[PDB]
Length: 185
Image 1 (cartoon, helix red, strand yellow):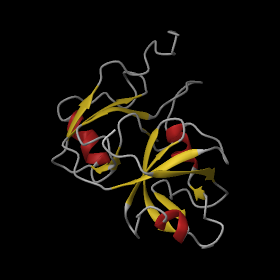
Image 2 (tube, one colour):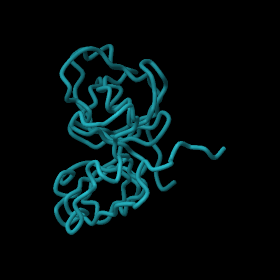
Image 3 (cartoon, helix red, strand yellow):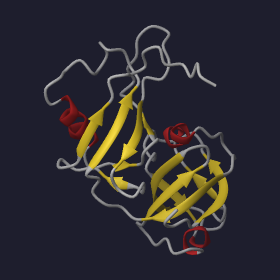
């Protein structure tokens, strides 16, 4: 635990545009209570670890203990509206090596090979990454299956929000959503 500074507030969310899964709207006190300035990098942790950026709340008075995020950011950690998550301020860097595990069938999206690891970088390039985070796919799926999302498991940075680049290295695991259902435990 090299550094741990954030606040405990409740995840917010309402009908709106699909984007906003990478921006946090908060108030001066929620962001200034620690040090977060405009456009600093913020990390979130309700059920899992999450990353995001700081934004100015429209209502500079209600956002003194609530964070408005998209359903995807809520899906990234696994919390419900009004839950309790801890958001800690951090900074961004260029991830040099990140591993992830797209949950699909061997014949869904990972049937390319040769440069497929770079293909993940090509799509995810210039993006904030956090081991154990999760991502969404352009509305794709098959029968009545579940998951169909990318789950990151390892990162090279200091486990802090980093932004991917074409030079970032990636790792893809050979055990996608095959026979995986948390049978253990």
